[PDB]
Length: 330
Image 1: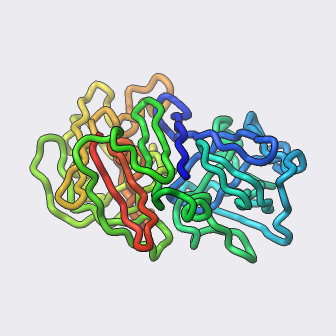
Image 2 (image 1 turned 180 degrees about the horizontal axis):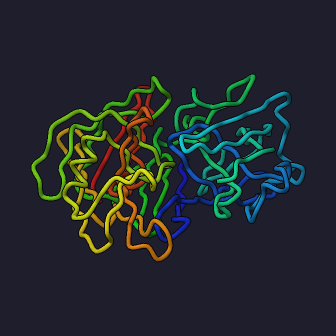
């Protein structure tokens, strides 16, 4: 089997991408944030505290003839950005772009933190990291990909995120028309439950390539590119007027400035992030200070190849017995 779904930016900055997901019988379609940095499929629901729902589409298990309570199961998650949610669990039929999993754990939110409430466009998350990170207790549950894997034509999914435009998540096949050149594959460590890999280095604009190992995660659920402070400083040093603002919480720059591209290494191959991808617009409405899309990972404890990086590539998440990551230009 295969599946193919369009993923759409939630706003003009590509702060996140939403993908429609069919849950239950008859189908209830929710727009979920596909997150290769986490491993829970959780949704706004009829069980979510009413005051914490503000425009989201909810899953109502009682209206699904295929929903079954996962008796005794609870879940609770906190994300790197300080947001969180928690609740109980149903199993139900979940379909993504034509691909159907029966018996998928659908984690129903009883509580969500303010950032989720305040984002009317995201109805929940669909985790695509390794199932070892799943928070369901007492019995850890499998991700949608883990459940589908054995049925897929090939045990892979691909992320093709757009810059200020829709893109595509495919399951079970590699669309050879969706990228240029070849796909370079690189090793993955699953020891922290992430799609964790090592970039071979970087370049700033037309500058020479610096060969240096940068361990990080391929995370579709993180907006920006977070790299070591040395790397980030070297980038913003090439932007006139750029500075790190403690009050704002990262590097800012005058919008009149031209942003250089940023290249990262995948083996001997190179992915070029165009400068425009690194512009996240005014820090506040009307401000001449723009927020940068490359920021320091210091104090996160891990480097994160988030959407800024991934949307410059066609990315293969290869769930073979020994997982690997593939990157192509496009």
